[PDB]
Figure 1 (cartoon, rainbow, N blue to C red):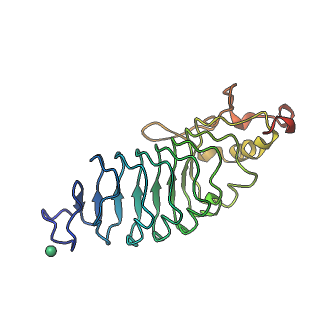
Figure 2: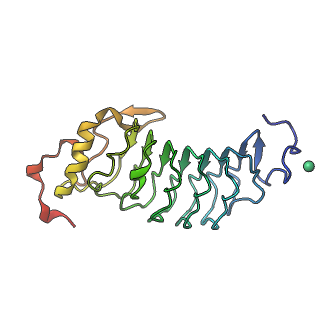
Length: 229
Ligand SMILES: [Mg+2]
């Protein structure tokens, strides 16, 4: 797939990247921004393990054939409105290990066919809503954030989920609103995963803040509405 030259691309291959077929690999090369001149036939784009602190609006608009986008292990503190809107063929998106605190409300809306969404190891304090409408998701990773609860009904349209990673969040099990997540895990133990170089089925991966007991085992009697924020 790498022909040993860069003649297949009108703009050549971006500096400090490698190009192989429709794969553009810019990993681990101290990039502080997305490199210019990424080939528009690109299907897989590796931008992970760099020092990207921000994305310019529109930076990906030309990459209409992109299937997989890896932005993990950068220093993203925010995302621009609409930054993924052109990527309507995208099936894998990795935003893990950044510094994201909030996301634009509609940031995932045009990724109607997304299959795998990885957002571990950020600073998220609430579920990005409308992950709710990503009905083709098989993989959802929210582990090691600061999530306290899941809005009632948030996962109910995700009928293709096979792998959910929720480990390492301070789930607020004293608050009676936890019961949606409690019941959802108990109903979906088969898809409760933790990662150890492979997917491990572990229904106790989601645990309560403080007590570290399994979220799925919470009793409604132990909860209270007045312990909610
Ligand atoms: Mg040429």
